[PDB]
Image 1: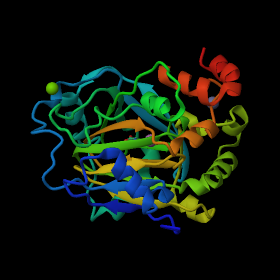
Image 2 (image 1 turned 90 degrees about the horizontal axis):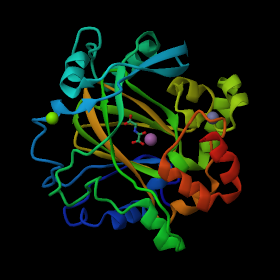
Image 3 (image 1 turned 180 degrees about the horizontal axis):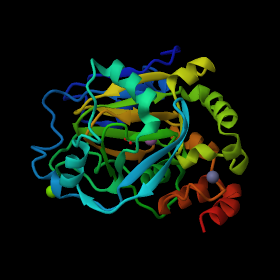
Length: 331
Ligand SMILES: O=C(O)CNC(=O)C(=O)O
Ligand SMILES: [Mg+2]
Ligand code: NI
Ligand SMILES: [Zn+2]
């Protein structure tokens, strides 16, 4: 079996190998990359996402989210308080302010230490889940706005024809902005490209061990667990690497830098934080190997997780028994 220790793999495709997205994902899995739950792909040196970022300040963050934490440094929840709209120019200036900027630090490890020590005492502002793309339309390779759609994958594999669309989202981060422990909707893959700015640190649990993380989370967030059978779908719970190590949860960590892609694999729990002002673009995708994960994916039926138009159809076709009780939560 390839990659039996479930290490995060880093790939360096050639420009020739960067032409066929599906085929390269299949290659990475042939080498065991999915066992980690997360892979890093460094694009060929010849490739560019776009010519420059020189006009990005005019993008609007309609609903910036202030991420307020509750709990202890290693085990906390975050709630998202909606703030007034601001441009990316305004946001970048805010990120660079004395109140919000990255603190002095020696290296990524010292900054990771400062994050876990001090995250809970601050409320950074995240511009998340903004529909859009920063890939140039003339970028033909690994353009996250030109991927094959999940609906088309389901049609190719299963013959069924469903409504829904699949588009990318932009994320504007600052120091301490946080993504809580989660898998993707319907345990899809994701791909994330860090367009510009400061790094993003990721933590991931191998898919084969995801249930271990879930069991820990029910012990650590016991009232949340009683309220919903899939509360990690709410995307509010954080657990530090120290706490994971204390409880024997297998995980890995890696830092993504500007210009790099990350791929999360089906049922690969992940969480992380931003080091400073940055902009990432991400989208869900499917392969044939996903279909079984989609059939088995948990769902939030408490009604908090409140999910997309397109996820309806996935549930309806792959999980017809759930369909009924799941859409009572989403209506
Ligand atoms: O970049 C972020 O804040 C969160 N990204 C993801 O969880 C992802 O790409 O799957
Ligand atoms: Mg602009
Ligand atoms: Ni994700
Ligand atoms: Zn729920």
